[PDB]
Amino acid sequence: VSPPPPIADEPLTVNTGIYLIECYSLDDKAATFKVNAFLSLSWKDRRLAFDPVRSGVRVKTYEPEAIWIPEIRFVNVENARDADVVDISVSPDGTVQYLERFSARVLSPLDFRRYPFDSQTLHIYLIVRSVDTRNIVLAVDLEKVGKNDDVFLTGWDIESFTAVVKPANFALEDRLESKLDYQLRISRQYFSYIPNIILPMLFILFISWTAFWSTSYEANVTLVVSTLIAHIAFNILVETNLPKTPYMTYTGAIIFMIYLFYFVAVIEVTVQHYLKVESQPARAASITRASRIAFPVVFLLANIILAFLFF
Amino acid sequence: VSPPPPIADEPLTVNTGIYLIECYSLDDKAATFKVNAFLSLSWKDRRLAFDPVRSGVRVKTYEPEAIWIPEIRFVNVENARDADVVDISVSPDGTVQYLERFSARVLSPLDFRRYPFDSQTLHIYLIVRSVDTRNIVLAVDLEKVGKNDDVFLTGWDIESFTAVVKPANFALEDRLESKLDYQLRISRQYFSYIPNIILPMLFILFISWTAFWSTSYEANVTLVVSTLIAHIAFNILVETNLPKTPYMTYTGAIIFMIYLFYFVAVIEVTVQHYLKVESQPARAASITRASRIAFPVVFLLANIILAFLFF
Amino acid sequence: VSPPPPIADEPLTVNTGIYLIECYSLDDKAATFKVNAFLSLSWKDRRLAFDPVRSGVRVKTYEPEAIWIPEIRFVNVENARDADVVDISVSPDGTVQYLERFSARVLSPLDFRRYPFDSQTLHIYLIVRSVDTRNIVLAVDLEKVGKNDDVFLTGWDIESFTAVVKPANFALEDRLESKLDYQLRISRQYFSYIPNIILPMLFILFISWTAFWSTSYEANVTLVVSTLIAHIAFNILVETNLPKTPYMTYTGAIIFMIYLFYFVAVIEVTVQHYLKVESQPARAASITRASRIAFPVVFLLANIILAFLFF
Amino acid sequence: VSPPPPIADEPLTVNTGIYLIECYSLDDKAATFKVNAFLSLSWKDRRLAFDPVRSGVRVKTYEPEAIWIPEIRFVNVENARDADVVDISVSPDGTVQYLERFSARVLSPLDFRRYPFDSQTLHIYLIVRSVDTRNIVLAVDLEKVGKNDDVFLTGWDIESFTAVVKPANFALEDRLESKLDYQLRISRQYFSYIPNIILPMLFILFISWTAFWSTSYEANVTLVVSTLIAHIAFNILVETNLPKTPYMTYTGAIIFMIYLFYFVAVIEVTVQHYLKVESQPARAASITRASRIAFPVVFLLANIILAFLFF
Amino acid sequence: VSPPPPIADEPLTVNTGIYLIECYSLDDKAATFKVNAFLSLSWKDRRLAFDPVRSGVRVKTYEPEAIWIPEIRFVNVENARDADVVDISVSPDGTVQYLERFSARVLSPLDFRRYPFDSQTLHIYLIVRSVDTRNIVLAVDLEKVGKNDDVFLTGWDIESFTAVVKPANFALEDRLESKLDYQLRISRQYFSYIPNIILPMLFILFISWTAFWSTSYEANVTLVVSTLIAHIAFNILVETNLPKTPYMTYTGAIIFMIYLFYFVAVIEVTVQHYLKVESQPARAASITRASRIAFPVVFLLANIILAFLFF
Ligand SMILES: [Cl-]
Ligand SMILES: [Cl-]
Ligand SMILES: [Cl-]
Ligand SMILES: [Cl-]
Ligand SMILES: [Cl-]
Ligand SMILES: [Cl-]
Ligand SMILES: [Cl-]
Ligand code: NA
Ligand code: NA
Ligand code: NA
Ligand code: NA
Ligand code: NA
Ligand code: NA
């Protein structure tokens, strides 16, 4: 079966729609997510036109093998989609209405700069390659673009599912390709990060600062070194949920900066002890008293600077 | 093959049933579970009706390809089900009795608020899309809804498997859809959490409170900081078994609150030491003696408040 | 093709056999194991009977599509088995001899009460569903039940592979089902647990008891708290290899009990220090000397009680 | 299609060959590895014999469906192999030359006794089941047995790929089976284990022995207990890369033995402190000075004994 | 269908091209990566040649089954590729233009010597096996070799995608094989390793060196032993992201060397304490003051040596 013939030198328009049924398995590290949706297609093929009286049916149901179906693919998928044809209906002017339900693992990069207060635009690219007989162009039927109410993605808020109505028509290997961009807008549910990572991380840091109210070097060393190890544990935990990025993330910046605070706290505790041993506790007392104010103040200001640069 | 014609403008009723054979792989983080079941379907096709006297046979067995079968799908599945037709039997009046055995990975969100003392309602949504010739409606045959006795789900008690008998009939892409809700009620076996997480967590916390019976700052620092690290280990272990939720869980709330108890214990140990060094051990003794009562009392009351808010 | 007709109102007996070739991937947490085996089937089809003299051949080989084959399934499988027909041979009296090689992931619950000194009976349930024409019953051909010598399951000893010869004949969805139980008896190789978990766990516990030969509170606190943290590590390691059970396991009981020993050791170390500070070291010495005997004695007796209750 | 008829009562010889193209995914814990190879088969079918003069062609190419092909399988595979026929060529005398490219996951147990200085023989068992018409025997064509130069297995040295030329001919379910053993000899690249596990483990152990040059009980307790915890971490790391074995491994033996050294070091540190407190430091000094020599000497000799028993 | 006949004894040239659409899942440990691409093939079949005037059409479109297509495979793939034919076009002179879209998991070893400042050349080997009728040789059509702009690989910079135009023609099992090498050049984004592993590792090491400004043995032991444990954590973290190599990596070398620095620091802290106890603090002070300079100087020089040897 060959493609439908043109009335004039016009290309064949294949109207498309995607209705999301199930959205799942957003793998942040992998930049992959799985989708289960309806894919609707519509085009005009005058070779299948019919007169109802002779046929006895107002619309005909064809099997995919019986008629010409455009070879529609997704660009940003791991493998060819898992598709099951639901319905093929032909009107007697030859307007075909195709519907399939598919599942596919989609590849769409994520921007982690504001993690875990980040938002993303997941893309689903629909494509058709033109044939030698005719050029095929994709169009959006907005009445067939949407998502189920129950659609959920663990740890995310689903904002919108829309299509950029104008296709990207270009040449690939001396043939026209017509590409459509379907956009799924999402925003991370940051809530959990507060009681699970941010506050525990702040608690251990503030615990290290109690060394500024102690002259016991041995206790101070135990305080700063133990809390540092706990900070290392949180750093490792965070980087297991994140991919390696060629940029700094918001959380990554805070985590990194906190190491500097632990490093200077160890210097303070060392300087304090050295002075005490040298019989200079008055100078050591001045440094410890200043540290009581300096450490929280510099921590607060540096965080304001970070929040400002990132948001 | 076209759908059965109506006697009047009535829709086609397809009676359904699901009998669970094997239930497994409940992935809490993923909100997915796997199912292996019988799917029974029943409808009337007058074109298939026959006289038992003339034909000789009481029932006719058909191959799926030979007759019209409604296109039944699951809404909340990752991929199309793995199905194998078991039997197709037709009665003399044209009543078709269809039976298949299928396996599918179902997507059903879980409420973790009362974790690990939580109960869940897993859903299995059956759906049919209406055709241009006729409208198709789903119904429940209660005699064909059930589960095997041996059905088990590791770490859960299976309470019931029932169906909401009235379908959700709605329009999707200008066609009637008839959706049925099959509910699998389960309740978590909390037992194991007690000796494995709750009691070990309480033991380390109570170990930190021994610092209220010690004047040794160095030992106190070792006691509170070491037990805090062990609490961090348990917090990390718990959050690896749970997804990120936009709400607080019961366990999450207790775990978070325990950090505050460790934080105040560090303050007490610091205040005590500072006073001793300042030659004020009488004031320090009053604070330590009060802490011996205050810490368990505030811990007990705060837990009563939490249990009340969550249950 | 319809089922063979009865001589009288007798049911059709399908003789079965399972010969294990490869056994692998026993997932303790999941209650799943993978199997690769021969499935042999035998029944009489009089319609297929022939005269050896007239036909010339002693046996006739058929393709599955050419003759009636019973629809045999496994009850406790994740998905329908991966099967490949090896041979179909028909004898002159119409006795069909069917052989296939299959692979399946089997679901069989495990009893962890005596872990890691536990034994299990893995089940493989064969089933046939009766048809409207006739009732089908399963039987065991003991000469076709066995396993390869090389069959191994990492961390287990394979004891036996036998079949319960009498089927469980019952009604499921108003049709007779004939179910056969194939049993694979296994016993865990506990060896490794001794040098890897049990002895290291005992060593750290005995290390904590050295605090009963020390008056240094700071060293005692370091001894008991550090070894407790190591015990927490072993507890976490153990529970990662085990599912969450609504009962206590043998290892779980020992692990839990050891927490109580650490808890009382912390009390002893605290009481000892408090008394020393109060200028009562003679009373403290009596408690420490008693602890030297009490702790190993109570540990030994409590273990005898546990071993008795569990074995 | 039936098997080739015999000239006399001789069995049909199917010459075989396996040429490894890609070898990957050796899972030590699972005893599985994946293979991608050419499988060559050759046999004589007199019914396919032709005159080169009359036919014109020197060789005839057939599609698998057109001629009789022996049913060849692998014994120790998880599932049936993924195969794609490359070529079927028939010579004038009726000698068929079959070639396919396949991929399979092979199950072959490993001996971990000398880990990580162990060598293994991975097996690939080829098999044919005899038919009622004729008996089929397997043979090795050594010119069709080999491996690609680029063949690599991460962390291993590939030594050889050979076949045991004489098959194991036996009866399974009253039919002859002809089994061939293909052996892939490999030897572990131990290099990495030295800087990553062995030397770090020795460093922490030697760090614990510095307690023999200290009278500070508190520092000694910190030294031996901290290094023991680090040894526990290495023990856990090692057992995650290894399956549970019913025998001792070389590394397992060294790791276990090192626990005894830590245990005796804790006894020494305890005895030393007890004596000092009892005003017996002269006796304590004799024990500590002896320990300085005894610990490295006993460690060196015990290792010589272990290396001797294992190699 | 047989291969095209030669005009003379010349081999059949099959022009090839690969256009990368999606590149993903680079598993460093496994030496595997997944690819989604267009595979273009072109050859001349004179038997398919036609007159444009007589036939009417300028090009003829065929279904794969209808004409002779060369059997093209990939050498270094796990399984046979997942392919879907897009277009087959025949020009009047018989020049066939074939296009398919495929996905495959490719096996390509990586050189970790300069990790994480390493670059790699991923290989995709295209191959054709000659037939008995004719010899088949592969060629590169450079106009059909490329990659999509959007192509990305998390944690990597994609440099180029080119082909070695001259094939590796060799004999395998007495038949010509023509192999083409497609090279995907990538370079690791080392950025993240700096704040996540390198700087935290340097911070803990520098924290251990504060013991050179302290006479407190107990605090020194806590400082060096605690930071060593944190270094062990980072060593374990690094080796989980890397495979076991028979060579030293850059990071591996630095990590290993840092153990020696911790070992000598423990010796210094021990020697210092021993001397103090022996009433020789003047000699101990000389060693500690020298260590303050020696440790950073030797660390800096050893790193210059390492960087020089590795880059
Ligand atoms: Cl697609
Ligand atoms: Cl479905
Ligand atoms: Cl089955
Ligand atoms: Cl196979
Ligand atoms: Cl391929
Ligand atoms: Cl050659
Ligand atoms: Cl050739
Ligand atoms: Na078509
Ligand atoms: Na049908
Ligand atoms: Na059949
Ligand atoms: Na300590
Ligand atoms: Na065949
Ligand atoms: Na072809």
Image (cartoon, coloured by chain):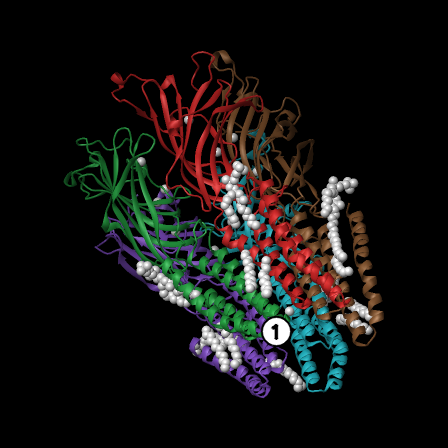
Chain colours: A brown, B red, C green, D purple, E cyan
Q: Which image quarter is the C terminus of chain A in? A: top right
Q: Relative to B30, is C151 on the left or the right? A: left
Q: Quadrant of residue A43?
A: top right
**Is disc 1 placed on a helix, strand or loop?**
loop
Check the image and name the residue furthest to the left: C53
Q: Residue at x 44, y 64 (%)?
A: C193
Q: Relative to E89, is D86 on the left or the right? A: left
Disc 1, ligand 11: is the CB inside 8 Å? Answer: no
Q: Relative to C84, is E109 on the left or the right? A: right
Q: Position of residue D84 (x, y in %)?
A: 44, 48
Q: Position of residue E97 (x, y in %)?
A: 58, 41
**For residue A306, above or below residue D151:** above
Task: Report which residue position mark 1 lands on.
Answer: C216
Q: Is residue E20 visible?
A: no
Q: Amino acid at mark 1?
A: Ser
Work out whether residue B263 or residue B80 is closer to the camera in this orientation and state it.
Answer: B263
Crowd rating for badge 1 (residues with CA inside 10 Å; few <14, some 14–19, many 20+): some
Q: Is residue B300 visible?
A: yes
**For residue B271, above or below residue E266:** above
Q: Position of residue A116 (x, y in %)?
A: 69, 46
